[PDB]
Image (cartoon, rainbow, N blue to C red):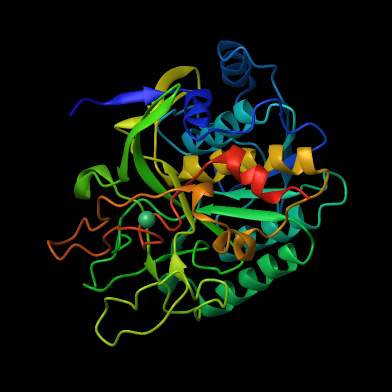
Amino acid sequence: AAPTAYTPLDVAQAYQFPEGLDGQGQCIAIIELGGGYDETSLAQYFASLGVSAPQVVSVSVDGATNQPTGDPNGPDGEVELDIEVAGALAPGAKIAVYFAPNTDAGFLNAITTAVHDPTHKPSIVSISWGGPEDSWAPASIAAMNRAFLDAAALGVTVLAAAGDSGSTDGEQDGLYHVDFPAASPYVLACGGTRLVASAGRIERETVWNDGPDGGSTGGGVSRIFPLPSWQERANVPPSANPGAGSGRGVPDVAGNADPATGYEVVIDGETTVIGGTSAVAPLFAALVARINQKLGKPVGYLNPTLYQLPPEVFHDITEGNNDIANRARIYQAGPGWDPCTGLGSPIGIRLLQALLP
Ligand SMILES: [Ca+2]
């Protein structure tokens, strides 16, 4: 195969994003635990995309500030990527990037800060950081979970990439682990795929899996969180780990993440190509920004509503697995919800259609 790339507008096109909407009146908050973002690269990208640059603002949490390392191959990548994909698709909204110490408490304080932020009042929050759910301090996970719940009951969407290491989520204990915050049931977990689409159609789209060296979408069965009531007709399989057990399946939806069909971005002055699920939360954060707009109200927590929406609102991914550890093929995709791509990739238009009164 040959590695390609899209700009953020092309992929939106692919997924039939509702046109004529930009996020105006809306405000997206993006969580960042390191690195920074340089204004030269941003303006260059927003012009290069023939889009009017959206307002970007930094918010210091527990000390942390906007601290770019100049290395396009380091944190900055993640910080600029998030703002570039998000800002290019919903240029109308207002970006509010929140930086915090990379600690269990900085991550938490950052979320609660944005979530209840009275000055920027974001309606959506995008997270592209995380970690095995079984590696976080239990008190941490419960704290954050509630932070999300508090978020829901506040009319605020919370999206988060599902990882970049497949079903094993980068752990060699020989078991399967899913990623947090993605496992939190109050989070719309974003998985990743390898999309092959053009202005008028998605030629193909499979689970994103480039082996051990290339990365693969995180996904599977939570071992911490029970099976949501709204996810009970999704046929989440039980864990593949010996002992089995029900669990909140991951992810909820998926979007392009395969670097080999990555995003074309501008990091620290360098024009390169980034991938991974980190691109998907902001990808869909912009989606929700336009939908909130047309509606004139925050769709807040979308998970319950999504799981019972009809088939034509989602493209179903059926080929592929996100197992980069063995030949067992766990987890494997198939018709309808699966532990690789969840409900599949959304079709914005049909999704806004589905949500209006
Ligand atoms: Ca499927």
